[PDB]
Image (cartoon, helix red, strand yellow):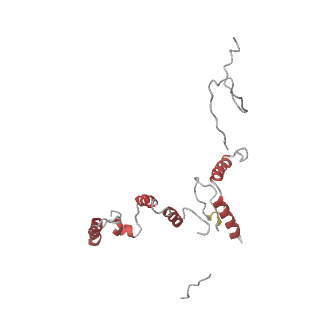
Amino acid sequence: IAPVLELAVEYVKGYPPNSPYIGSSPTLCHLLPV
Amino acid sequence: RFMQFRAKDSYSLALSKLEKRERENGSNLAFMFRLPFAAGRVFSISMLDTLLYQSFVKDYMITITRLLLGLDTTPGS
Amino acid sequence: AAAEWISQQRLSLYRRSERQELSELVKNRMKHLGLPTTGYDHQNTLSYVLINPPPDTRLEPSDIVYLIRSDPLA
């Protein structure tokens, strides 16, 4: 094992449009194109 | 204890004795050794109250839980 | 390079305030119902009632004076 170093239909990706409530944290999700 | 109940099962019936012994010693985690709970088959919302009471001593506990659950999304987290 | 745009929207959406959250909810409902977003575009005022003030009280702008108007038909 290498040692840890000290120094370092297809879906679109977007946010859900209609947030159901205030305070819903926007998470980038797998979204349908339409 | 009633989630997946095998009445003709000595092991699941012996877990009652272990749960009673832990409850004798004043343990708040007594349901812990039930098989459905340990396998993630059951949880209660009563744990969320314990999360709130812990926040009186651990002001970070709520934030940590939501970060694990994805409830709050901080960039770089 | 789409991740750069995703990161830009992520920081913007994280920085947005609660007023923007309430504004976009109303606008989302308005476009759903078909109403224009514009026109929806807060109350930094304090109001009270002075019943029968002394005749020396100064009149301020935007004051509303309660009146008892005599009967027009009488």
Quadrant for the C terminus of chain C, please.
top right
Residue B76 image position (x, y, % from top left) = 61, 69
Pick whichever, A3 or A17, lies toward us.
A3
Residue C35 image position (x, y, % from top left) = 70, 45
Q: Is residue C37 left or right of residue A6?
A: right
Residue B28 image position (x, y, % from top left) = 35, 64
Q: Which residue ends up furthest to the top in the rendered image? A: C74
Report the label total: 0
Q: Is residue C47 left or right of residue B1?
A: right
Quadrant for the N terminus of chain C, please.
bottom right
Q: Which residue ends up furthest to the front in the rendered image? A: C56
Q: Residue at x 68, y 27 (%)?
A: C57
Q: Residue at x 70, y 31 (%)?
A: C63
In the rendered image, which quarter is residue B30 located in?
A: bottom left
Residue A27 image position (x, y, % from top left) = 60, 63
In the rendered image, which quarter is residue C59 located in?
A: top right
Pick whichever, C70 or A14, lies toward us.
C70
Q: Residue at x 59, y 83 (%)?
A: A6
